[PDB]
Image (cartoon, rainbow, N blue to C red; front, side):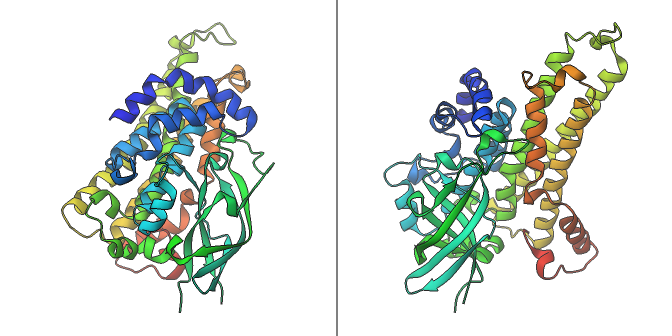
Length: 385
């Protein structure tokens, strides 16, 4: 696809901004510019608003490609890049507000329901504090989760202009993905009109998409597939970056003892093992999306069990890839501990990415297995499927 070709062209420029975005804990303007100009955030955007409506496979592969160059950029592409997908089935009025003048206007996250929306006439009033708002300095709107206080939805996704919230400085001093600048946001009491909200349960279960009735199969994909897809793709591509870094170093490396690493059977076979695991994650994650897309294109319904199994695969894919990156980092030696070498940055980024809520494994493994035994997950055990 064309976006990935444009990324390949500026690959050296992207790698060129990485150290500085990390030092700043925020993508440099040049780093954000490289992504904005490449069209990466428009991957899943409606064509009406300059977007490409790519197949999920293309989105996933592009994120992985960006992530292998600079983990922070890759991560921001996979998160900020998913927001146009959901907005596609938000009220036409908010899509016009966000993209009407400038198609390249970005939305920040998180969807975590960290806020409280008080229903008032015409909409809601919002108060809360959210964390992990990736790429937020470069966004002009936020898409946030909220619970509804005291005939309305129980939970919402709400859209706010940057004018209506505060980015909290010094709230992203973390071990990895430093360059994402995933700062806290605070809202003291912002009015949010009804047309700038979606009911979160309807987003999850397909009812918001049915109400919008779009013809494009892309926009009828399950939320539980699409939202975690960018995030786990970023983790996968980060580990592919680490592997690439490791290989580049190992080719010339002569070890503490006198031994050339390119002649070391223990280290070389362990590289093969890790590369096999990381590939298994890439293919697995993408296969779910291919198949879901095929069913949606065919007008066939994606079942709860199918969704649950897809989440299971996606979670397992993140974990497999991170563990594989750990195995090669442990064999990279003491020189790989230094900040002046890139591998360690990919390695820490992968671990930061693994801490995201979409990677918690236990409940989903349990719930998907329960559906396979003929049982029905109840209540909270149905969340994020």
